[PDB]
Image: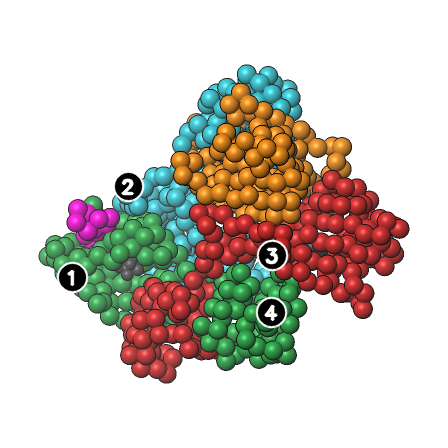
Chain colours: A green, B cyan, C orange, D red
Amino acid sequence: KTASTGFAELLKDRREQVKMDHAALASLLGETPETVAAWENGEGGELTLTQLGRIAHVLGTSIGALTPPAGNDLDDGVIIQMPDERPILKGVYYVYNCLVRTKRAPSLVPLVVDVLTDNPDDAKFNSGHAGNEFLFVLEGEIHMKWGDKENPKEALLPTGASMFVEEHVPHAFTAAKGTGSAKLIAVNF
Amino acid sequence: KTASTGFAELLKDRREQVKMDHAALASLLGETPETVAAWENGEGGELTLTQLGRIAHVLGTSIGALTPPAGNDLDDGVIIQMPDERPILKGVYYVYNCLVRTKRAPSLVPLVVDVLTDNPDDAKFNSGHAGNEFLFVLEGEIHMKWGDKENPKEALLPTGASMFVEEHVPHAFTAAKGTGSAKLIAVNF
Amino acid sequence: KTASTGFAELLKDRREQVKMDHAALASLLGETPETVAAWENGEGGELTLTQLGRIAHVLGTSIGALTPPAGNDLDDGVIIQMPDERPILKGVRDNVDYYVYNCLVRTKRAPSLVPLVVDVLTDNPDDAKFNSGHAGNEFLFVLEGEIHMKWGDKENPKEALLPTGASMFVEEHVPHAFTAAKGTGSAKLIAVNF
Amino acid sequence: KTASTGFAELLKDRREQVKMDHAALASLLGETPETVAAWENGEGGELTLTQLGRIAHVLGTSIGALTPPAGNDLDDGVIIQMPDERPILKGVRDNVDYYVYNCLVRTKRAPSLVPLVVDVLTDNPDDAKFNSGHAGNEFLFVLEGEIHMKWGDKENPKEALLPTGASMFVEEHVPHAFTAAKGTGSAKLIAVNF
Ligand SMILES: C[C@@H]1O[C@@H]1P(=O)(O)O
Ligand SMILES: C[C@@H]1O[C@@H]1P(=O)(O)O
Ligand SMILES: C[C@@H]1O[C@@H]1P(=O)(O)O
Ligand SMILES: C[C@@H]1O[C@@H]1P(=O)(O)O
Ligand SMILES: [Zn+2]
Ligand SMILES: [Zn+2]
Ligand SMILES: [Zn+2]
Ligand SMILES: [Zn+2]
C-alpha cells in the first residue's frame, strides 16, 4: 500500500527477475549493496523522482512497474458517496459536481455538470481526454460540438438523450441557444 | 467488418504466424488446400461454431483471435441516442431504460432503472456481473444490499448519492421502506 | 463441443447484461425464444460464422466476446517437445528455398508464443529477402554459424553481422531479413515470436 | 529528466481529468499553486517516492499512471547483443553454485523479456533446487547436453529428461528446477522469460 513498501517488494522482484544481486544493481546506481538492500527493506521513501527514473532505467523498465497500484478504498467491493460529500469546481463556463471515484478504477470520473452558457458560439472545446465518456442530458437542452474545432460536427440534445464520446475526441457543450442552462451527467471511464 | 472478411484475414495471419501453408492447415481439418484458400478468400461464411472451434484448436488459439472486433458505429468518435429510441424491458421488479451503447466499447451498458419495490425484504440479488458499475440515485431513496446474500451489507442512499460496484460483486436494489419507488441511473463499464 | 458450451455460457452472460430476455433477443434475430434457450443450453454447435456475427451485432459485441479462450494443453503448467516431434515447414520467397522452419513447442495458454529453429540456407546477403514485419515481438539467437541481418527500410536497411551466440530483438511490424554471412553457406537461428 | 518531463505532463493530464485547478490540488497537498505549476513545468525532479504517493493518492490513481513508460532503446526497432557483452551472474541456492546466468539482449520496449543462456552445473537430480515459480511465462530450449527437469509440487514433482534440441514452456508462477541428466556433468539452457 505505502509507496515505500510497494516499491521495496517490486524492486526485489524486478532485480531478481533480471538476475542481479544487490552488488550488481548497486554498481549501476552510485550506491552500496547495503543501501539497495535497505530500499528493499522499505527504506526507499526519500528517493527522488529523478533517482527513481534511474533505478527504472538500469532495470530496463518503468517507474510504474516498480510502484504499487492506486490501492483499495472499497468496502467489500463498494464505495458510496453521499450527496453533500462532493466538491464544487469552476470552468474555466461549467460547474462541476464530482461524484464517487475509486482507486480500484482510477479512470472512473463521474460528474454532474451545470452548463452555464446558452450561446453555442461561446463553446470552449477541450483537446479530447484520456478515457471514453458516457453522457446523459439531465435537464434542458444541450448543443453539442465535437471533432475538429475549425469545422465541427454538432448535435441538439433534448432532455434524456444519451451520448458516447470516444477517447481523445475533442468536444464542447453549451445549452441550446437562448435556453439559459442545462444539466449533464458525465461518466468518464 | 463482416464475419467472413474478418475471419478470412485473421485466418491467413494466424496460419502464416505458425508457418503453415494451405496444405498443412488443410491436413488438420478434413479439407483440401483449395478449401482453406477459399476461407481466406471470404468463403468461410457457412463454417459452424464447432468447425470454428476446431480451426482455432489446430492453430493453437481461440475463435476470438480469428474473428473481427465488434465494429465501428461511431460518427467521428460519437454515437448519440435520442430519448425515445430506447427499449423498455422487464424485471424479472425493475424496469429498464436502455441508454446509448457502442461497439467501440461493448462493456458500456448504461441504463435508467425504475425500482418498483419498496420492501427491502423482496430485494432480488444478482450473482454479480462482468463489468464495473457506476450508479447515481436520480429520484427518491434507494435501499441497497451487496456482497453475500446470506449476510449482506446494506446502505440507505438519498437522492443524488453516487456509488461504485466492483465486478462480480453480488448486489440488489429496492426503494427505501414504504417510499414507493426510486430511480437509478446505472453505468456498467 | 467445449466451443458450444462456452458460447452457451457467454451468450447468456451477455444477453443478461444488455437486459434482454429470451423473447427480445429471439425477435431481434428472427428466431423463437426456444431456439435461443437451446443455444444457451449447449445447442449452438451448428450456427454459422455469419449467424454468429449477427448474434454478436445484435448484442453489440464481438464473436470473440461470446466464445471461450483457447483451452489448457499443459501438464501442471508445462508442455514439452522432443526434437523428433517438430513440425518442419519450408520457407520459399521467390522460387528460392530460403528458410527451413523447425517448429518448437507451442501452447493454447500463450497463443502468440511461436518459437523456431530456423535453418538459414542462403549465404548471399545481396539476395536477402525481407518480410513485411509481423504481429509479434521477436527474440532471436544465433545458434550456429554467422548471420547477416537486415532490418527497417529494404531500400536503405540497417544491418548486422552476428556470430554464434549473438542475440537480437525485433519489435513488432519491423521488417527484417536474414542470410548466412557472405560465403559461409548456412547458419541457424532460434527465433521466439511472442 | 525525461522522468520529470513525463510526470509534468501526466500530472497536468490527471489533474485536469478530476477537474481540479492548481489551487485545489495544491491545497489538498499543503502546497502553493505555484509549486504545483512548477511540477507541471518539469520541476518535479526532486520530489520523493513518499511525496509521489501522496500526490497519486489525492489524485485517486497510481504513481505509475503519473510516470512515463520505459523509453525506447531500439535502433529502428532492433537491439542486438554480441556474445562478448553478456552480463554474467552466479546462481547460488544453498551454498551450492547451481546455475551460471549469461544475460542475453533486453529492451525497455518489452521489459518482461528476459532471455538467458543458463549453464547448468549440477548433475544430480536428487539435489535439484526449486524456485517458487516466477512472474513471467517461460520458453526453454536444451542448447547443450541433456537436462533433467522437475516441476509442480516439489514433494511430488512431474519430471522430464530432455536431450539437446528439446523445447519446453513453463507457465507463470509454476515452480521448476533443472539439473543436467544424472552423471552427465553439465548442460545448457536457453531460457526466455516473457
Ligand atoms: C468531463 C465532462 O465532459 C465534460 P469536459 O470533458 O468538457 O470536462
Ligand atoms: C445493471 C443495473 O444495476 C442493475 P442490475 O445489476 O441489478 O441489473
Ligand atoms: C522468424 C525468423 O525471422 C524470420 P521470419 O520472421 O521472417 O520468419
Ligand atoms: C531461467 C531458468 O529457469 C531457471 P530459473 O527461472 O529458476 O532461473
Ligand atoms: Zn469530456
Ligand atoms: Zn449491477
Ligand atoms: Zn521475424
Ligand atoms: Zn524459470
> Amino acid type of disc 2?
Asp
Label pair 3/2, CB-CB below 8 angstroms? no
Which chain letter goes with mark 1?
A
Residue C181 quadrant: top right
Q: Viewed as shown, does residue C104 lie left or right of C38?
A: right
Task: Tell us which disc is closer to us: 3 or 2.
Answer: 3
**Which percent across, then down, holds residue C125?**
52, 34
> Amino acid type of disc 4?
Leu
| Distance in Å between CA atoms under marks 1 and 4 | 58 Å
Q: Viewed as shown, does residue C155 lie left or right of A136?
A: right
* Residue A36 in view here: yes
Label pair 1/2, CB-CB below 8 angstroms? no
Q: What is the secondary structure assignment of the residue under circle 2?
A: loop
> Amino acid type of disc 3?
Glu
Looking at the figure, which quarter contains the C terminus of chain A?
A: bottom left
- Of residue D61 and residue A33, the one placed in the foreground of this image is A33
* Residue C75 in view here: no
Q: Which residues are magenta?
A: A139-152
Task: Tell us which disc is closer to us: 4 or 3.
Answer: 3
Is residue C191 part of the magenta span, yes or no? Answer: no
**Label 1 sits on residue:** A117
Q: What is the secondary structure assignment of the residue under circle 3?
A: helix
**Label 4 sits on residue:** A25
Q: What is the secondary structure assignment of the residue under circle 1?
A: loop
Callouts 4 and 2 on one subunit:
no
Above or below: residue C136 compared with residue D83: above
Q: How many marks?
A: 4
Instruction: Using the image, tell me which numbered label, if any, was put on residue D85.
Output: 3
| Distance in Å between CA atoms under marks 1 and 3 | 65 Å
User: Counting residues from the N terminus, which is met first, the one under dot 1 or under dot 4?
Assistant: 4
Instruction: Using the image, tell me which numbered label, if any, was put on residue B75.
Output: 2
Label 1 Cα neighbours within 10 Å, binned few <14 / some 14-19 / many ≥20: many
